[PDB]
Structures are given as C-alpha cells and as structure tokens.
Length: 450
Ligand SMILES: C=C1C[C@@]23CC[C@H]4[C@@](C)(CCC[C@@]4(C)C(=O)O)[C@@H]2CC[C@]1(O[C@@H]1O[C@H](CO)[C@@H](O)[C@H](O[C@@H]2O[C@H](CO)[C@@H](O)[C@H](O)[C@H]2O)[C@H]1O[C@@H]1O[C@H](CO)[C@@H](O)[C@H](O)[C@H]1O)C3
Ligand SMILES: O=c1ccn([C@@H]2O[C@H](COP(=O)(O)OP(=O)(O)O)[C@@H](O)[C@H]2O)c(=O)[nH]1
Image (cartoon, rainbow, N blue to C red; front, top):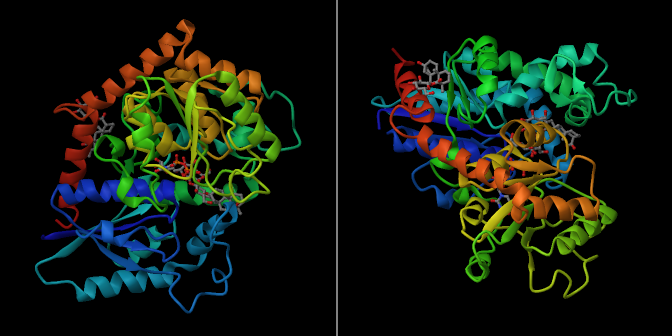
C-alpha cells in the first residue's frame, strides 16, 4: 500500500471503538494503518492482523505523573489532561522514528487523533504532518462547548446558582438550564480542556464526526461556521460493529437466551463503561425493572455499584424468569437482535448512535458530561426515547419502560426510531450524506501530499 494513516485514540472504550471502526473503513479504502496506543487499556492486537500497533507514552519505566494513576474507576481519566500537558516530546519522537524507518515507496498521508488530544496539533505541525480530528461525541455537544463563554456570562456554570433549572437556556432553547449544569458540573477541569480542544480542532486539516447529517441537521451550520477545515459526517456503526475493540470478554451466552424471547419483548439495559451509582439508586433501578413487568438483559460492569465488587446487594432469584444480569456483551450485535424492543442507556454517544443505527428506541438516564445533552436532543428533537431527567424513582422507571415498549401512546417513539434507522441506511447509498462524506474524506486524504 502506497499511503499510510497513523491513528491515535484516547484509551477508553468510547474512544477506542470509533477510531478502530474508522481505521477499518480507511483500510477498506486501501490505506495501510498504524495505531499509536498507550499500554493502558490496550485492545487485543491479535484481533487486528491487518494493523500495526505501536505502544507509546506509558512504557516502563513510567513517568512520575502517570506511574500511580488508578487503572479503573472515573479517576483513570486523569491520563487525558496529563498526556496533553506532557506527551508532546514522546509523540514527536515516535512519529519521527516511524517516518525514518518507512519504505521509500510508502509515505504517511496524515495523523488522525481523538479531538481530546489537542496537544497533537503542534506536534504534527512541527513535522509538516497534517492532523485530522475524530469527534467521538455529537455535533450538538460541540455547539454547546462553543457556547460556554455565553453560558458562563449567564451564571449557568455556577453550581451554587440553583435558579431557572427547568427553564429553556437563554440563546440555546433546545437545552434546559439543568442540562448545562449537569454537563459542565466539572467546570474547573473542563473549562481549560474544552477551550484547547476547540482551538486545536479549528487549527486541524479536517474533522471526522461519528454522526450523520439527518441525525443532527440543526447543528451543521454551527460546524461549517466554526471549523474552517472540511467536516465529514460518517456513522461508523453503519459500516461495522466495534466488537473487535472490546476491552472486556463478551458474554455470548446471551444470544441463546435472546433466541427464546418474542420479538421486541426485551429491554436492553447498560449504564456505560465508567458509570457508578449508590446502593440506594441501584436497588431503585432493580425495583423499576421488576415493576415494569418487561423481560430485560442488564449489563452491570463490576464497580457500577458503590460498595460492592458486582451486584452483591441483589437477592438470589430476584429479577425472575424475565431478567438476566451479565458483565459485558457485544452491544451493537445485541441491539440488532429481533428480541430487543428498547434500550435503557446512560446516553453515551456510541451507545446512542448504535441504538439509532439499529432502530431501537431509548430510555435515557445520564451521568453528566455530554450525556444529558445527548438525552435531551434524542428525547425532544428526534423523539426516539424518554428522558428520566429527575433521578431514579421505581414508578417513573416502570412508566418510561412501558411507554416505549408496550403503550399505544409510545407507538410514535417506536416508529420514529424505525424511520431514523432507515435515514441512516439511505445516507450510505450513492448520493447520500454519509456516502458523499466518506468519498470526499478518501479524496481529501489522498490529496494531502500534493
Ligand atoms: C475530557 C475529560 C477530562 C476528564 C479527566 C478526568 C476527570 C473528569 C472525568 C472529570 C471528573 C474528575 C476526573 C479527575 C475523573 O473523575 O477522572 C474529566 C472530564 C471528562 C473527561 O473525558 C471523559 O473521560 C472518560 C474516562 O475517564 C471517558 O470514558 C469519557 O468518554 C466517553 O466518551 C464518549 C465518546 O465521546 C461519550 O459520549 C461518553 O459520554 C463518555 O463517557 C470522556 O468523556 C468526554 O467528556 C467530555 C466532557 O465535556 C466530552 O466533551 C467528550 O466528548 C467526552 O468524550 C475525563
Ligand atoms: O456490554 C457492553 C457495554 C458497552 N459496550 C460498548 O462500549 C461503548 C460505550 O461507549 P459510550 O460512548 O456509549 O459510553 P462510555 O461507556 O464511553 O461512557 C459502546 O461502543 C458500546 O457498544 C459493549 O460493547 N458492551
């Protein structure tokens, strides 16, 4: 292969999944692929015989700043600001020694990084290497990030200012003030990171969005105005699932059980790769699921429940014939199964987009960050699910589950989910928004060394 692309993911499941989907799509279009990855949270390189992996930044002996960071729980994310602040010299060395070792017939077209690796723009510039960015969250979230100076002036980023919570955000009516308060509760850290991510995204050679035009049409004018480089909207789950980049072992025994369920009769439940609840909330969720009287498949990550290794506070036999708990599944393959009638999600963007791409309507909870904005946009603009926006109450959980899966009152939500899947499929046909985004992206990358 004449042309090589280097990709550099953020080493968490919601970041590795889209960049290895993109890597596969670009491999399919005839590019050779090198992945730069931390040893931390590495995927199974044996699943990618067609890719070269290079492990960087946390090789032994480890830096003072990274050596003792926890490997699980939300605190593991401290690696993101630390690598941005201290990784530039090592990334430049690794890019240089790859380009020095390269064959004379092959050249590196570009570096594609996660948008959160804002430090990589200056490194790529210093080597006369073009950098493209992969956005792993929505255009709507980007629109909110660019509006932060206005949210700040209005006092929405003040945790102590508990006024106007149920009102429409001034200058941003698609959001309630409480959505902004939730999304930016970690304002001391996010203020600096998001400003840098925006500046270095605007400075990049091109922005790839894991989305499609018909999903986020209201947000296109903002990205065309804010980002001078070309934007490409490609819905990666419509190209392939992320099964090969799983960081955990799949429980595949779930498919034999799904095959025993009537069509659209199962609630799939998963609150993410990082999320945590109190025992009080975890038992309130469990009661809501039982109160619903619907069949369910619930992925609970070890550490989801504060105080327990897994699901110890749950009684044996509880959940009935109706319910299964597992540690991990191939989630998009589960969403594609005919048994699935709905998905109770934490509203992470990969989970939200996979559900949309499989036509599965949603019940939304959130654990902050971009989650409350995804839940608000999908529930109120697209109308493909119900937002549980006032915590965990067993009655409200039961009503939301029944509304989406059974109630005639919820038929419009099930129909909206069906039609949005169809729009995603049409977007991949010749002349479709996603087809044209991908053809343009391939032509654009092929032009970078002219
Ligand atoms: C930018 C980030 C800096 C970061 C550093 C660590 C920090 C925390 C977690 C804040 C609390 C304190 C502290 C110290 C901590 O508890 O560790 C802080 C904010 C979110 C974070 O990125 C988040 O890091 C997590 C690992 O700890 C990832 O698992 C998240 O990815 C996942 O990525 C998915 C794909 O983007 C996303 O939909 C999903 O919700 C998310 O859970 C990713 O979400 C990012 O949050 C940003 C918040 O503004 C968004 O702009 C980005 O689009 C989004 O990707 C991690
Ligand atoms: O049991 C599971 C649970 C989740 N996932 C995948 O983990 C990713 C989670 O990404 P998301 O953006 O939804 O949220 P995060 O977990 O990053 O907060 C998605 O690609 C899911 O399909 C999976 O494969 N199996």
